[PDB]
Structures are given as structure tokens and as C-alpha cells.
Length: 223
Ligand SMILES: Cc1cc(Br)c([O-])c(-c2cc3cc(C(N)=[NH2+])ccc3[nH]2)c1
Ligand SMILES: [Ca+2]
Image 1 (cartoon, rainbow, N blue to C red):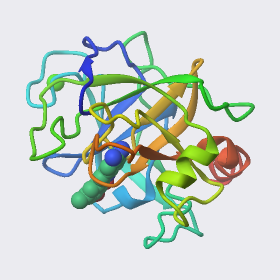
Image 2: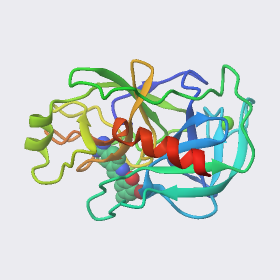
Image 3: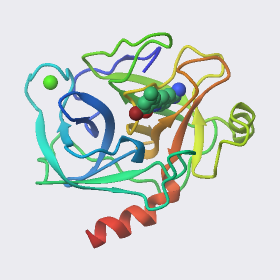
């Protein structure tokens, strides 16, 4: 997260860290045995870390559970990142409490102007890599479809939305991928891509979760 602030330990209880010997993507806990992340974060050997704040120190509240399966959306396209969503089932259910809790899926899509909270342990520099030890937060508004499409002509599908600042300086970045975009207490986006990080006129692009709620429910129900 570039231009964001320290969230404060466990203030984002649905945030998870996907770890393969190091933190590589974020995710959101939606029930005690399932997490939603981005299909481009897929790999084998994933351990899900819940109740995390400082990813390099065990401080208490952490729960490390291995992933039993990862279900990448069948129509995920790695070249356009259309349908960039993935579900991870946990080997055992997490213990939910106030530090580890699930987030609700939306009932309707959000409108431009809605303010949302984006969080993650991704890069904090737009020019160079600087990965933090504690969780960072950023409040960003969803942009209108014309501004999103004028920013990425021909690269936005109806399963994506832009959120951020066209003036630059505040944005999600590499390492934040798979993580949550929460608006009005509902999971509305998944950090997906952008051109560079916090660059002027190049806002972040997020997977539009309201378009996948029936898919998530049917898939969890059959697995
Ligand atoms: C090289 C590389 C590898 C992975 Br995997 C990423 O997720 C990314 C990535 C870039 C990137 C940029 C943004 C943004 N809002 N500007 C958000 C997520 C991102 N993820 C970059
Ligand atoms: Ca820790």
C-alpha cells in the first residue's frame, strides 16, 4: 500500500496473509473454512496466516492453517486478468473471535464515490520495493466507469472497477494482490492490478465481487 497508514494490530480481522515461506499475497476470510483471494496469486504449498499484524514476528493471535484446495475461477484469463478471483478451502476451520472474523459478501454492487478500505503488506514505494512488517491501510473511493475506462482503454471488463486517486501518491501495490476492498462493511473488491503503483492517472483495478456472489455460494456449497 503506497501512501497508506498503519492499520493497528487486528483492526482488519478478515485480512489473511498467503505464505509459501514468505508473504506473497493477501486474502479475505469469508467463513471459518474459506478465504477469497485473486487467481493470479495461485500456487501450491500455501499456508494461510490469520490474526496477523507483524508478519515477521509471532506476537499472539495468529492462526497458521494449510490450504486444503484452491479453486481458481474456470474462466480466469491470465493475459487480461478477467475473472481474477480464487477460493481457498482451509485444512481446518479457523477459530473466529474479535481478532479473526469473516467479512460479508455484498448484496448489491457499490457506486462510484463510495469510500472503501484497502489493506495489505504489499510494497509501500511506487519506485522501488519496501515491504512493511505491519499491516497498512488506505481509504480510497470507487471511480466512475468513464474515468476507469479512460485510464485503461480496452483493458477493463465488466468484472473490474477502479478505485484510488488520479492525482497519484496513494494506491495498493504488488504484495497487496488478493486482498480486500471493503465498503460499507461488505467485501466489494479484491486487489488485482494497475500500471505501476500510485502513478498519476493510473488508478488500481479490482475484481468486482458482486458479480461472483452466486458462484462463490454455489462453489462453497458443492466443496
Ligand atoms: C510483478 C507483480 C507480480 C504480482 Br504477483 C502482482 O500482484 C503485481 C501487482 C502490481 C499491482 C499494482 C496495483 C495497483 N493498484 N497499482 C495493485 C496490485 C498489483 N499487483 C505485480
Ligand atoms: Ca505476527
